[PDB]
Length: 466
Ligand SMILES: [Ca+2]
Ligand SMILES: [Ca+2]
Ligand SMILES: [Ca+2]
Ligand code: NA
Image (tube, rainbow, N blue to C red; front, side, top):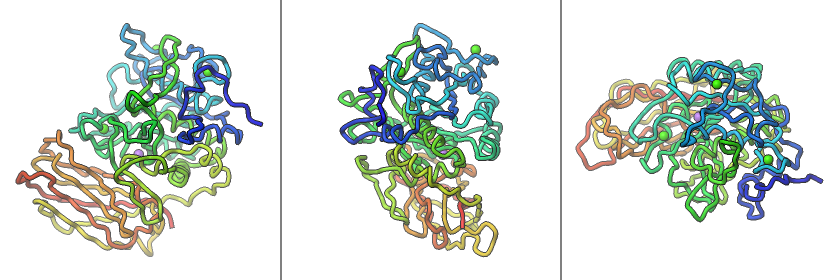
């Protein structure tokens, strides 16, 4: 009985609905009756053209603000180069108006969309914190297609205020259910960047989203890491189609590309999911993604089955998001038990790294204590170490059930001699596994050079339930 969008460009939105069965299965969600009605999504970016013919109808002033110029109007700053068209393109992916004879449609075409202009100026910690913490009780989902530089040699993340904003968000946002933070995993593929060296994507508070090309391949810009949760389609080579969305100056574009286009699609699917079940917490949402994401159709050389039988890849997380499955599972979902946190400091003495270091430790996962965990969610390996050439290192973490998470792959451009200072490498690959047993940390020098350094701290942090 459901009638799909009549928008002129909808047929070109191959990733939403297609006969080729290689899409995000969004029409199946719309058919079940979910279009994002009642949900509020905010695009933290370079502004939003609120008067765009395909956005005005869903624009929400309450989900918007201009942090760069300190005013409530997020209108982009126009320039000959159209530098500030990025936020508008991301906004259209999430909630472009449907059946209005203009461009295409958003994943959640009935959702309310707002924008925070915060990238067009000095992006300070305060600027970030005010954006992430904007109207936490009105906005449900925050989408961010930006982050630290992808030169493949930086290690950076949120400063204190932004961290506090994230924490306040998941704790108090949405009436205590927790703000949903969707993050683009990065465009550093050509520089061999790792998204675990990015504190925003690496955070347990954000759903880090990677990309897949139309033909199901790992895009050139893609960054691999264990913190990524799932994937949505984006651009690839010139024989592959790209993302169709709203563009600056009230135009329509069929060339929105890179990691930037994936997070918004995920944000849209999550909006449909919240409509299906408004009581889902920030953790419930991550559980739904893990359970419903599909690897099939995605090519990668590292697909591996984890301890609970799910396929995972460092390029895709658990695979492609499936909107129909997301909204279906959401309706019947029982809120997960309170989050427990088990801290296990592993080292009893510093360890020389040399050419290779292996640290084994059998843990009980806080057995007999209030934070005993039998069903893992995120896991962090907080490492502090010195090394002469950081990029030559490759670090792996093996769970008791045999799941190998590569916390850090070699980064050829990273010649830093600063090592890691209590950096929290995170992995989503052992989700739902029993964490008790022997964990193994492996640090190896991937180069032939005679490198040297010392691992002075290894703290294993487990999050989960019993
Ligand atoms: Ca303004
Ligand atoms: Ca439209
Ligand atoms: Ca990066
Ligand atoms: Na994350």
